[PDB]
Length: 366
Image (cartoon, rainbow, N blue to C red; front, side, top):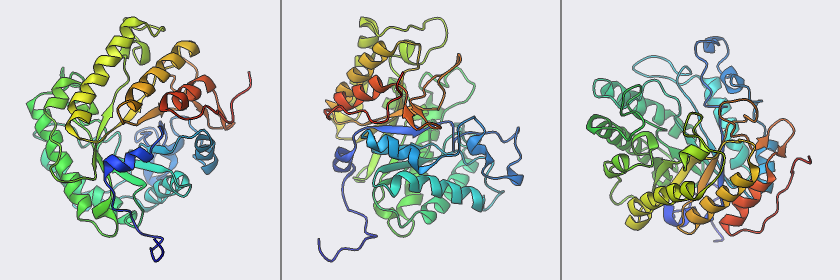
C-alpha cells in the first residue's frame, strides 16, 4: 500500500467494484435538460441545467443523499446544443466546465459517479445516419475522456443512453436488425475511443446499453457484449412493472398487486438470464415508480425490487427528476431546495432491501 500515488486508479474488475455500490440516484431533468429552441445556448451555454425547473445543482444535495447511504450518482447529460460543427464537434468550454463541477460533487465525496450522453439528437439507431453518428461519438468521447483522464475508478462512463429508432413502431418494443446493428456499432466505437485515451481511461469502467437500454428479449438477444474486457458493465433501464411504475394511460394502477409482482419477477428473470447467469456485470441505471399518492404500495414495491436485484448482485439507481406535483412523471425523492427526503419510507425500503441498517436522515416532517 505504502508508496502508492493519490492519483492511482485501482485495477479491479467491474464485478468486484460493483460490490462497493449500495444503490444510486440520478440527477434527472438537470444536465440532461434540453431546451435548444426555447433558450439560446450561444448566449449562455449552461442555462439548460435549470431549464426544466430544477435548481442549480449544489454539493449539499449529494451530501444529503450520501447521509442516506446512496453512493452511486448518475449524472445524465445532454451534450446536443453545447458542441460545434464538423469535423471537430468541439464541446463548449463553459458547458464542459460545469459538467466537470457537477461530477466533482459526488466524486470528491468518495462516491461513484456515472457520466453519459443523454438526449442526443444525432445518435439514433438508423442506418443512413450511422456514419456521422460514429464520427461524432468518437470526437465527443475523446474530449470527455481527455477532460477527466485523471479521475479514478469511481468515475464510470456510460457511452449512450437509450439509442433506438425514434418515432417508428419498433422504438420501444426492442428494435429490429437495423437498430440492433447500429447500437452495437456505436457501443464498440465508444469502447475503443475511451480504452485508448490517456491517463486512467484504459482502466476506466464503461457502461454500454442494449437497444433502447431496454429490458426486453429482442434487445437482450441482439446485444453484443465484449470479450475479454473485465471493466465493462451492461446498462439497463427498467421501470417494472410498467403499469404501476410509469404508465400514465389506460392500463395504469396505483397498487402493487400480485400481477405487478409477477411482471417484475419476469423482468428480473430476463436480466438474470442474460447478464448475471452469463457472468456479465450489469447496473440498472434507471428505475423508479411515480408518486400516485400511494406511499405504502411504493414502499412495498421498492423493498421487493431492491431485495430481488440485491439477491443477484445488481445495483439500481433511482430516477429522480425533481418532480413531485402535477400529472406527468412524479419521480421526485429529494427536495433539492430544502434538502429533505420527501418519501422517507421509500429510502428505508431501499436501505432495508439492500441488506443495510435502516436510517433515513433529513426526512421531511409532515
